[PDB]
Length: 73
Length: 76
Length: 45
Image (cartoon, rainbow over all chains, first blue to last red; front, side):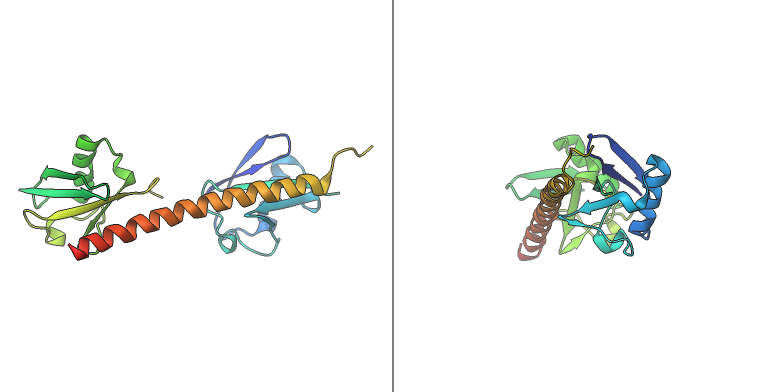
């Protein structure tokens, strides 16, 4: 499945995932691709920040869905 | 045989088909008269949404039947 | 040193995400409404 992650500069990252992937998995992918530690990643979707222990399925994040990535310290 | 396709906008379209025609093919014929992309089409017959893989005879859609059309953004 | 605003861009992301979700839902909803209307037509006449 393909999803997107929009960053602050407007630069968009595309990820190939599975509906059973957890948010921590997604943060793992973003780290592997962008070099950003999961500790500094805040992922927002549908008006809220997503939690590490849940799946994309739990948030009804479908194909082509766009996730917003904002950074922490 | 001919069947009719109805839109909610009140338009009635006619189609020449064979009992052996598949729903995929029916949508193709609609596309050729209305321009509507086949994957945006949803055909409803007697309360049932028709699947692309079956044929008219699978649904016992006989001559003179009326199908109802409504759209979706895309398939999948 | 630090010059940007974390909770500010955090708020923006929430809002844009919110809007985006409302858009998706509205789309799914109209598509369901159209489907319901076609089913009613096919059974009422």
